[PDB]
Image 1 (cartoon, helix red, strand yellow):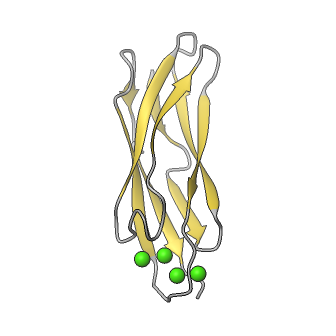
Image 2: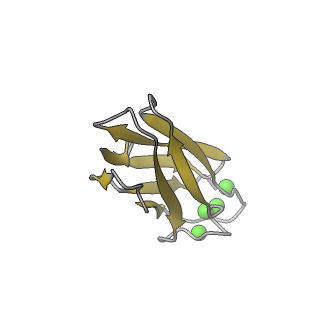
Length: 111
Ligand SMILES: [Ca+2]
Ligand SMILES: [Ca+2]
Ligand SMILES: [Ca+2]
Ligand SMILES: [Ca+2]
């Protein structure tokens, strides 16, 4: 069992409100599996550019992907391109992560 981000890169608009992130499970599909994710600060900041999130992604037997939305924080203040990262971790017993196993998000400014 392998798990990774697909898409691994996300290009998002500051006005976009929310975007879906997607993690995929490959190999044996027949057993329950899970992986934890957590946003991580980059040149973009939790609290000011996006709202931080940590979670558990559960894959029941038979399901090979999980999606989750992340909220982008809009404002009226000019910036240039900025990144933050979502990272995977604590995969359940059978699981080994593959690349990408950290997703990259660029917030394109609009102001
Ligand atoms: Ca910023
Ligand atoms: Ca911003
Ligand atoms: Ca804006
Ligand atoms: Ca802005």
